[PDB]
Structure formats: C-alpha cells, structure tokens
Length: 95
Length: 95
Ligand SMILES: [Zn+2]
Ligand SMILES: [Zn+2]
Image 1: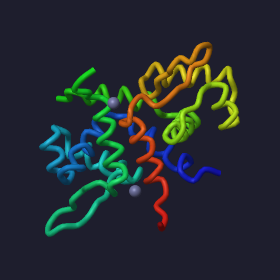
Image 2 (image 1 turned 30 degrees about the vertical axis):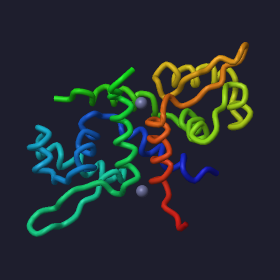
Image 3 (image 1 turned 90 degrees about the vertical axis):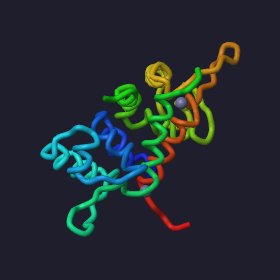
Image 4 (image 1 turned 90 degrees about the horizontal axis):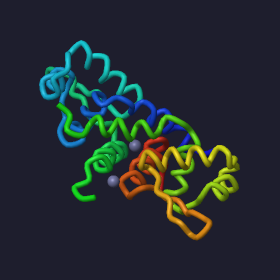
C-alpha cells in the first residue's frame, strides 16, 4: 500500500509522445478544442478527435460544453505543473 | 516544429516503470543510495546498480562521491516537481 505511486504509473507511461503533451503545454496557458488545437499545432481533426479523448481517459485532459462547441482544457493544476517542469528540465538557459 | 519537445519525450524515456519512480518519490523528501534504497524500499543491490545507474544516465538522477560511497539525488527541482505533482493528481484528499 502506497496511495500515490499505484495511481501515477498510469500517468507517467501515458506521457510518452511529443504530440500528446505539446497540446497540454499550450492548454496550461490557453485553452483550445480539437479543431483550434489542429490549427495551432498542425494536427488532423480526425487524429485529435482520438488523442484529446485519450488524454481525457488518462485525466491530464477535460472536455466541456461552451456556447456552440466543446472546449478542451487541463483537468487541474497538478499536472499542468508536472508538464511545465518537464519542459523546464529539457530547456536549461545555462549549463 | 518542436524546438525542445522531442528532448522532452527523452525524459519520458526515463519513466515507464514502478520502483524507478517510487525511489524518486522518496528522493523528493530525503536522498538515498543503492544499499539504503535496497533497505528503505525493500529492493535488491544487483537491481539498484542498474536502475540508479539508468536514471543517473538519463538525468532524472545525480550521484555525489563520499569516499568509497556515493550519495544520490534528483537532478534538479524540475524533475523533483514532475514526480511530486504526479503524486498529487493520483489522489485528491481533504486537508
Ligand atoms: Zn532541470
Ligand atoms: Zn489533481
């Protein structure tokens, strides 16, 4: 018994594609849906119609209705702060 | 276009396994090495001499020499923030 480990193993393998995370990267500062995400990040709407639903099913992502589309966003500040710090580890301004 | 992103899958290609990051969970409050990880997580020395070394050689981990010993750590507060923010979206309890 561990509580934490035995529930983020599910996160820390699902992270493993640069496309997936490049989207949450952006969401963590500004929200887009499948169709805007496809414009901003050069991805197909068919493809994001299945990557956004997967991110959602590992709970880094959340869907919501708004006016006359479904907006997508980060589930909560936890993993937005995980995902910020992977970029920070990968881009040192001075070594 | 990516600038850095595929160097960030290159730190996801450091995760993907259980005790590997159950170690680093604990390094995220106190620093421990091969013999003492193998004591404190009930592990084995053949094994930690491959996993402390992988993580070391994929920069989520850094050693420090103390004569015939080496103490070991996370690499910086970036990777310490990745694994502790994951260990925060795994459960969400009252405080
Ligand atoms: Zn760093
Ligand atoms: Zn959370």
